[PDB]
Image 1 (cartoon, each protein chain N blue to C red):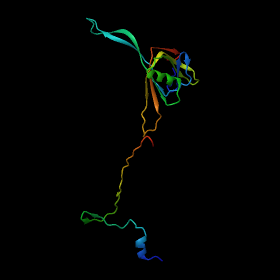
Image 2: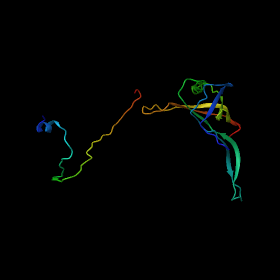
Image 3: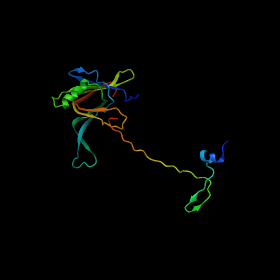
Image 4: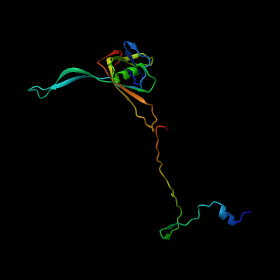
Length: 49
Length: 148
């Protein structure tokens, strides 16, 4: 016995229902991708390990 | 006419006519060269030909590279000369070996003088073997063998 309110709180969300706002206007889209964040790594080694 | 490869070789140092058995393995030995120094002379009415006049002969230097290892008689001689002690000479025989460890070509150097010892950098980011670089200056070269 699982109530719909439980699903809205505990279950993971699917990808297929979304709304996209471009500027101050909303436009229907079919696919949106690429929202990734990347960082570089700076390293430093010394003689004593 | 079969050519010879350049990655199998051996060098022997003789100190006071006594060979050093621990100083035969080296990572690299530079090539040996001889040059006949000449000056070009031009005549008065000769404007189409050249004349080259011979002079003394110049020998090259001997460079070796080797990793850091246990102290050997070659190391002790180099340290003594570069510590300010009396200069000493050594005789070197370079041999190019074939598949049966038979020297097809050999070069002998008379009265080689240690003049430089150098070592590689201590790099914390490197993956390499610490390598010593030695250079000697000799008096005369003359080769023996069936190949050259």
